[PDB]
Amino acid sequence: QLQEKLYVPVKEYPDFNFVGRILGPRGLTAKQLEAETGCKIMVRGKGSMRDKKKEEQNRGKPNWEHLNEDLHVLITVEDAQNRAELKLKRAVEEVKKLLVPAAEGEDSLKKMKLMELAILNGTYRDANLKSPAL
Image 1 (tube, rainbow, N blue to C red):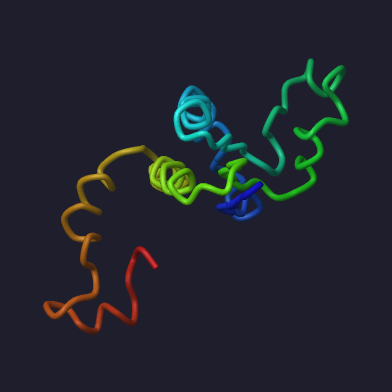
Image 2 (image 1 turned 180 degrees about the vertical axis):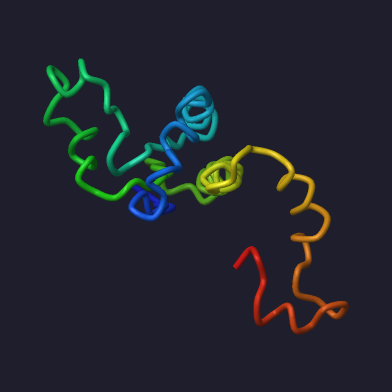
């Protein structure tokens, strides 16, 4: 299969729960992505299926298997279709706006369309040496 793992260093963000951010209230979207894109985007690292019931009975399984990795979001698409990966990558890219340690899941949506759309450009030039969204 094909997997693309978008790492978020949970060691870097102890105060930002990417799990509570990504699959917490929006776990539905992870399900929608696998259902629609054909890619089962699994959050790997510590906290994927961190359910107490799971560590009891579902223990030893993929959830804990990748629990020993660092928290990252992985679009796992089982197929060779490039059209497949294109579909999950766009969806997961919206997650890329989500796995940001931002306090909220907005503002950036508007700011990135406006300014972050073209950060370094003729108007700035030197901003190329230091852009916020590197």
